[PDB]
Length: 304
Ligand SMILES: Nc1ncnc2c1ncn2[C@@H]1O[C@H](COP(=O)(O)OP(=O)(O)O)[C@@H](O)[C@H]1O
Ligand SMILES: [Mg+2]
Image (cartoon, rainbow, N blue to C red):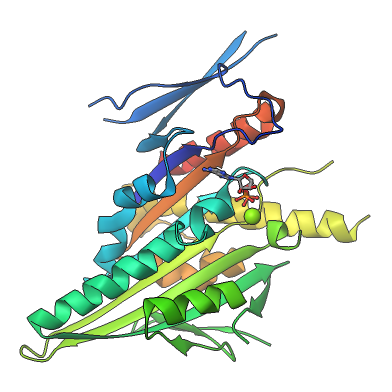
C-alpha cells in the first residue's frame, strides 16, 4: 500500500541551546527532500524523506499536507498516521496540540466534509475508540481486552473497549480533553467511518488510526529494563512490518503483525488499499544528536 515519511524538526524551546547549524534542510527537489546532520569531532549523515518540515512550519501548515490523506478515509480507505521519535521531540505536540493537532484538525475537517457530503445524499455515521498500549497490554482511555480479527470481512475490534458515537466537533473535543507513562506507551485514536448514499445505495467504509508512539530512546531496576524491552521491540516490530509491506514482493512475504499489540490491532489498516504516513519528530538540540540519528535511521529504513 501507500507509505509516506515526513520528518519534522521542532524549534528550540526557550531554555534549550538555540543553534541549529548542525542541521541542513535542502529545499524540496523535483523526487524527495533531503536533510543532512553534521557532527564535529566532522561526520556527515544524509537522509531522504517525502517531506521535511522546518522549525518554522506550523501545525496548520503541516495539516494541509495530510488533509487529502485523512479525507480519503471517507472514500473507503483505512489510514494510519504515526508520530515517531525520542521523548521531547514533538510527537504529542504534533498529534494532540489543542485545536492545532493532527487529531483535532482531522476531526474538524472530517465533520465539515461529512456535513458537506449531505448535499450529495451521503449519510456518515462515526465512532471513536481511544486506547493506549503500555507493556504490550491494552488500556481503554474512554472507559481485559483482546483483539478480534475477521479475515473474511477484513475488520477488527477490541473486546470491552468503549466505542463512542461522534456527534459534533465540539463533543469530540471534550472526549480528548477529558482523556511519564505516556512517554512510555503508544496512544491510538481510532475513527470508524461508515456511510451510505441515500440516492445511490452506495456504501463506504473507512478508518482513521492516529498514533502517538512511545518514545524511541534506548536506555542504559529490571521492571524498567523489561518495560524498555517491550517498547524497543514494539517499535522494531512496527518498523519491520511497514518495511515488509512496502517491498515490491510483499504479497510473498511473512508480515509479523502478531509480534506486537499495535501491529496486530492495526493489521487491516496497514494492508490492501491502505494509506500510511509516518512523522519522524526530531529535536534541534545537538546534545541529542545520537538519538536524533537513530530516529532518522529508523524512519529512512521504513521509507526505503
Ligand atoms: N513544533 C513545535 N512548536 C512549538 N513547540 C513544540 C513543537 N513540538 C514540540 N513542542 C514543545 O516541546 C516540548 C516537547 O514536545 P512533546 O510533544 O511533549 O514531545 P514528545 O511527545 O515527543 O515527548 C513540549 O513542551 C511541546 O510543547
Ligand atoms: Mg509525548
